[PDB]
Amino acid sequence: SGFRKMAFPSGKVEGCMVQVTCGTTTLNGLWLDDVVYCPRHVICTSEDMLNPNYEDLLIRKSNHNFLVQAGNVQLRVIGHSMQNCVLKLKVDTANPKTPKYKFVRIQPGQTFSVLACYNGSPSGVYQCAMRPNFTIKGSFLNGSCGSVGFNIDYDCVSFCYMHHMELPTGVHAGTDLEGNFYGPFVDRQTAQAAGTDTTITVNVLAWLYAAVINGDRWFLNRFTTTLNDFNLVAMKYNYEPLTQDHVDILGPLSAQTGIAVLDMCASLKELLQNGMNGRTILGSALLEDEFTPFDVVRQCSGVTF
Amino acid sequence: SGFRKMAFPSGKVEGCMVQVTCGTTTLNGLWLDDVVYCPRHVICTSEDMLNPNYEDLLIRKSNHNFLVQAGNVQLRVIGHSMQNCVLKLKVDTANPKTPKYKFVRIQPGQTFSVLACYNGSPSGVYQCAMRPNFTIKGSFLNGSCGSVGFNIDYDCVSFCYMHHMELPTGVHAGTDLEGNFYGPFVDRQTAQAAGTDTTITVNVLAWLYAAVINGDRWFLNRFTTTLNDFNLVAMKYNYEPLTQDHVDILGPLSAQTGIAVLDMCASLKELLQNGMNGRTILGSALLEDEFTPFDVVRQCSGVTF
Ligand SMILES: *[C@H](O)[C@H](CC(C)C)NC(=O)[C@H](CC(C)C)NC(=O)[C@H](CC(C)C)NC(=O)OCc1ccccc1
Ligand SMILES: *[C@H](O)[C@H](CC(C)C)NC(=O)[C@H](CC(C)C)NC(=O)[C@H](CC(C)C)NC(=O)OCc1ccccc1
Ligand SMILES: [Cl-]
Ligand SMILES: [Cl-]
Ligand SMILES: [Cl-]
Ligand code: NA
Ligand code: NA
């Protein structure tokens, strides 16, 4: 038993990380098959970043302006192109460690693992959620750009996130691997703000099922609620609305524990209106919303890859 | 910026995990060079586990009673031996993925990454601390035994933990890679209890420095304290004593932030006596003690491997 914020094993991704240097700027790239993906702002100076014209900047660059280094090996760039906010550098050697992979755009609330890298080398791995305001609360320092987020499905790596910037609040923004930002953000150093973040209600309920599975039951109550009445309370505490689709996705956890989804909603309702009274749930004094229903099933049934 | 519970990249360890089957019992082994390490209770039946005589049980086993499977490859066992609570199976093939490694016994308070595995395959990776009562609060299901804990130092994997059992409280116990349990526990299914757990004071202070580095400063106060006076308060809240060695280890964080260690102790003192008043520190309503001082420096300076 036990319940931890668990990341995916990172070896399949570690074997894809490289270092991309253009001019004096160095960040990470993702080497799949014969293409290296990296944030396009690698082609900027420290001065360009206020409002760069990336089209113009890339036109002035030749293949040999991009230094791509896999470990100590030197990769030869034989082509370069821009797709939205990411650079695609064609190299002369396919990565022999290329896993089976897919590029996917995740939805707010879904979780993934981040392999935080500097200079093409891994620093650490951690799990996090795409917030409802399309930011993530990561741990990223200068040079971490080009670090990727991912999920694993049996043997297939689903890449969903490439890191590009930090907004003043310590919050992090990036793109999918097709180069489109999550949220309204742009890769230039002009003033930008994330907008209203809310709590991922379906994930909190998932985590309450996780607590029951692991023996924390004090919050189960005799009350029940309707879906609309629950959302009346949720909205007041800046929780995302719970939809019928969310109810369906919580179905299997409800079946495993024998606690109807609306009965668990009624328990959450009381927690929101009364607090925890200095009690804890899975060691936490706050309601946790970075576990999806599938994250709970995976970890509590021991799914492997 | 940002601060997350970060695990080490797990690829070097993933390449060492195998599946060991004896009779009907299957757990994980660690394949380094030409030796596979696994928990010795793999040689028990479901009935033996009450009070096995492992010496006797192993004597009745032949090399071919141990089925060792690396992926789909079948390893040949050519030798078997017992060191304390772990089995050492000699195989006919060195692991080609063997990293540079060391076996180390960590001390209470120190952190490591756990690569949770089933049937020799990774399920996930998470960071945790050796509690003062020599247990860990992990996430382990049946079949997870033989999963290992580890740290990385540049290129060297320091293996410190092999998982063996769960005590009734959902708490987890295991050995170092020489087979000796952390704590007073024994690998048989007789009644056992962990004993008094306490909060890892030096780690909480580390995490308060981490909060300052990341911009949370509301808890810094004008007060100061002596080391003995702080420990008078700490003991009352079941915090481990802070020693002069702990002060020295916090030195570099104190120098980076400009906050003397005893001034941070004074801030912790007020937090303990007054609570947080519904405030949070790095998103947490409770004081976090699973980060060592070096974990904070690593993550906040971007150390790589
Ligand atoms: C890439 O490694 C690096 C990672 C960060 C964690 C530092 N990203 C950048 O340097 C990035 C490059 C630009 C061209 C996309 N810039 C930022 O992320 C920048 C961070 C600095 C200012 C600390 N943030 C930024 O410009 O945010 C928009 C903004 C600007 C001005 C006022 C408010 C908000
Ligand atoms: C190995 O994969 C598995 C992992 C656990 C997470 C289930 N470990 C065991 O099966 C282990 C084998 C014994 C011989 C060391 N047994 C236990 O960990 C056992 C767990 C069961 C009872 C759920 N725990 C145990 O025996 O604890 C001691 C005990 C016994 C009786 C009363 C209180 C405490
Ligand atoms: Cl309804
Ligand atoms: Cl908390
Ligand atoms: Cl003193
Ligand atoms: Na209603
Ligand atoms: Na004193």
Image (cartoon, coloured by chain):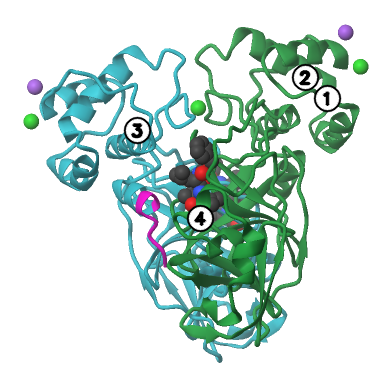
Chain colours: A cyan, B green
The quadrant of the rendered image in which ligand 7 is seen is top right
> Which of marks 4 and 1 precedes in the sequence?
4
Mark identifier at residue B48: 4
| Cα–Cα span, label 3 and label 1 | 36 Å
**A186 or B188: nearer the viewer:** B188
Q: Indicate the amino acid at tag 4.
A: Asp
The residue to which callout 2 is attached is: B265
- x and y percentages locating residue B61 in the rendered image: 58, 73
The reply to whether residue A55 is in sight is no
Q: Chain of mark 1?
A: B
From what the image shows, is residue B33 above or below residue B173? below
Q: Is residue B80 inside the magenta stretch? A: no
Q: Indicate the amino acid at tag 3.
A: Thr
Q: Residues within 10 Å of mark 1 (few under 14, many from 20)?
A: many
The residue to which callout 3 is attached is: A199
Mark 3 residue element: loop
Query: In the drawing, does residue A78 fall left or right of residue B225?
Result: left
From what the image shows, is residue B292 above or below residue B94? above
State the extent of the magenta-drawn residues as a range.
A299-305
Query: In the drawing, does residue A37 fall left or right of residue A140?
Result: left
| Cα–Cα span, label 3 and label 4 | 49 Å
Q: Are marks 3 and 1 in contact (CB under 8 Å)?
A: no
